[PDB]
Image (cartoon, helix red, strand yellow):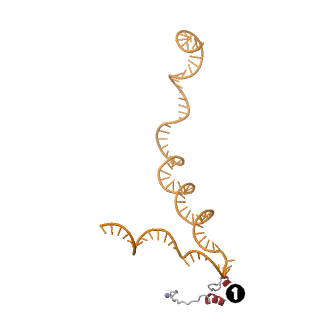
Amino acid sequence: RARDGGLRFGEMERDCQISHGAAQFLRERLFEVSDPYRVHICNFCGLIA
DNA sequence: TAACCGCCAAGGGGATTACTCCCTAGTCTCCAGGCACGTGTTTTTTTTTTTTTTTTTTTTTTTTTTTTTCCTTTTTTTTTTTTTTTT
Ligand SMILES: [Zn+2]
């Protein structure tokens, strides 16, 4: 709380959300509101360009 | 005390001569086990793959949340400047 940190979306949260089977909440909590990024990738090599 | 010698007596069987006979020496003639040559099938050796247990390695240990405390080098060797003594 002193560093103003968010809650821990742990393993069993992903387990019970897979049990509910709603993919959009998983895509929100684990990609949209945690650490989104955009990278550019070469098509032939498949690595970071 | 009976070995040994001398003397005498008796008899038993090996040597001798002749007749016989029969078994083997010798000589063909057929054929068959004895032997020279080739080889085997068990016996030992060597590989080969597995087995079975032991040892080693590696990975694991429910989740979330909130406060402090200590530390986040250190000695040890080398260098470089400074100070003092001498001619
Ligand atoms: Zn490329």
**Residue B46 in the figure: left or right of residue A22:** left
Name the secondary structure under disc 1: helix
In percent of width and height, residue B52 lies at 63, 63
In percent of width and height, residue B83 lies at 39, 72
Query: Vertical placement of B38 versus B85: above or below?
Result: above
Dividing the image into 4 quarters, which one contains the N terminus of chain A? Answer: bottom right
Q: Amino acid at mark 1?
A: His
Query: Vertical placement of B71 versus A32: above or below?
Result: above
Quadrant of the rendered structure where residue B63 is? bottom right
The chain under label 1 reads A
- For label 1, count other residues whose C-alpha is less than 10 Å away and answer few (under 14), some (14-19) or many (20+): few
User: Is the CB–ligand 1 distance for label 1 below 8 Å?
Assistant: no
Query: Vertical placement of B38 versus B29: above or below?
Result: below
Point 63% across, 90% down: residue: A28
**Residue B82 in the figure: left or right of residue B87:** right
Quadrant of the rendered structure where residue B1 is? top right
Query: Vertical placement of B47 versus A31: above or below?
Result: above
The residue lying toward the viewer, choosing from A13 and B12, is A13
Quadrant of the rendered structure where residue A33 is? bottom right
In percent of width and height, residue B23 lies at 54, 35
Reading the image, the residue beneath label 1 is A20
The residue lying toward the viewer, choosing from A16 and B63, is B63
Point 66% across, 89% down: residue: A25
In percent of width and height, residue A27 lies at 63, 89
